[PDB]
Amino acid sequence: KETFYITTPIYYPSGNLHIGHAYSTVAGDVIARYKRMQGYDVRYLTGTDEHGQKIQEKAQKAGKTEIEYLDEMIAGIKQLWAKLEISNDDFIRTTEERHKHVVEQVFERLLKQGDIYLGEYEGWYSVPDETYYTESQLVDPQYENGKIIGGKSPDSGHEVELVKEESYFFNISKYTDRLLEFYDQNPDFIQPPSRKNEMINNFIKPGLADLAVSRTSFNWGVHVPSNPKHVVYVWIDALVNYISALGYLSDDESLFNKYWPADIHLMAKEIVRFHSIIWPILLMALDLPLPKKVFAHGWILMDGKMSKSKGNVVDPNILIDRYGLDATRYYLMRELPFGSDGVFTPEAFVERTNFDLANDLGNLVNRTISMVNKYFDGELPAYQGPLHELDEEMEAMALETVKSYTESMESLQFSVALSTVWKFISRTNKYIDETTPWVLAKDDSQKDMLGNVMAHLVENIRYAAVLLRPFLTHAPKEIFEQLNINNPQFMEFSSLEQYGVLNESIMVTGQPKPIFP
Ligand SMILES: Nc1ncnc2c1ncn2[C@@H]1O[C@H](COP(=O)(O)OP(=O)(O)OP(=O)(O)O)[C@@H](O)[C@H]1O
Ligand SMILES: Nc1ccc2ccccc2n1
């Protein structure tokens, strides 16, 4: 059993998670389920990032300890994943010891080695944006004696002021040629291609500046063992969740020894830099193998991209409660091409939900069961061969739909994988219009052919349902329940290699009802 390790990022609970966080986690579950159906030993991880100055500020505002603020927020997040039916194998929290021990030890090791050195951090903080800007990338600069003394933010235009404190730095520039050599040896490391260019051209080529990895202005966080005044900053703390959750540096490294390196790291494009540059360099200094792929998908837009800070938010609980689980998951995996951006509209949601699920697929199944109940009393005839003339091309189309499904899935374009599946569904509906089974019913002479048409409809659906198990968690099962396919074998990918596995007659449901919501 070949291992496949997949991770989502660890999300910051400064506020409630929205459809964008859902979108990443949902995509990871799709890969996880897909990969399990191909017979991999899968580990899929998600988690939270629980340290920093902001978690004090939100917890002390609500009137509670930092941890009992987090406990509430994590309980709400675990609930959202359970409701989305995320098949994550673990939840990692940076506030738990298996993580904290690893951050402590990695920091000291890089201190021992001389990768890290004590210095002073200098930057420009904007209160509105909650972002730190460098001297150079500042806009509308003010000079006093020829040095920038004050300025504006690039992204808002609010006044900033300098921040200066003691900080440990990670000298990463010496790993630059090792890192570029890594990109050349592993040409699919950064996905998609667009993001790899902007990594080389905008960060590495200018010169990778030393990285401020610790702070003194707050206390909530992992403290540096050799210097308690310093508390570890976001990069080293958060990034090592991918390995700490596997029991790295613990009593039991068995999960680390078998699952690391990561087959794929999911994220949105704002943090590709830390996964494709800093994370591989950190692992080099730890002398550990690098991840095999980092994937940055696009943004859900609204005004701007969806953020919890700015409130332009859609709660996935509202969408699931209203329109259903399978609709919500479908919308996220269908409307935005993996890697491109896209704008959310509740009108686009409802059209996807209705036109594809309810009207194309839901109606296909209902007509097919209805007709089988009508003409053969519920007793579906067995498969034999491509007796109708449309069947040669259509039986072949089934197989080619799986070939095209696979490569869209391997290459991570699930929107295209889903649209290819739906092309087959739409054609299955057309086959009813083309064959006209109601005309075949009148002649008792036409009985094999009328049976063949139903056998082809049912098999066409089988294929679609089978291929949709990674995406939709109720819909496939409900279709199998109503068709009354029973052995698990015909729900797996293997059973799609040769067309027409049902050569035994089966009694479909006498009471078909809507598949969705
Ligand atoms: N609009 C979005 N589209 C896609 N993924 C998103 C989006 N917002 C959040 N994510 C997911 O969460 C990760 C980081 O979350 P992030 O802190 O940026 O969310 P946020 O709501 O923008 O937070 P903040 O309020 O601090 O800006 C992304 O890498 C991605 O996995
Ligand atoms: N460990 C740590 C410190 C500060 C943070 C700020 C923002 C996100 C995560 C953080 N983690």
Image (tube, grey):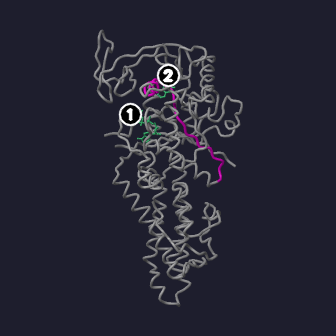
Residue 276 seen: no
Q: Position of residue 200 (x, y in %)?
A: 47, 33
| The disc label shown at residue 211, or none | 2
Judging depth in this view, the residue of 129 and 257 nearest the camera is 129
- How far apart are the alpha carbons under marks 1 and 2? 25 Å
Tell me the SS state at disc 2: strand
Q: Would residue 441 be found to the left or right of residue 383 on screen?
A: left
Tell me the SS state at disc 1: loop
Amino acid at dot 2: Leu
Q: Position of residue 295 (x, y in %)?
A: 51, 41
Residue 436 seen: yes
Residue at (58, 79) in percent of width and height: 381
Comes first in the chain, label 1 or label 2: 2
Q: Would residue 63 be found to the left or right of residue 261 on screen?
A: left
- The quadrant of the picture occupied by the C terminus is bottom left
Mark 1 Cβ inside 8 Å of ligand 1: yes
Q: Is residue 49 found inside the magenta-colored segment of the image?
A: yes
Residue at (53, 53) in percent of width and height: 409
In this picture, is 504 found above or below 112? below
Q: Which residue is mark 1?
A: 309
Residue at (52, 90) in percent of width and height: 444
Mark 2 Cβ inside 8 Å of ligand 2: no
Specify start and end residues of the magenta stretch as a single range: 39-59
Displayed quadrant of residue 254: top right
| The disc label shown at residue 187, or none | none
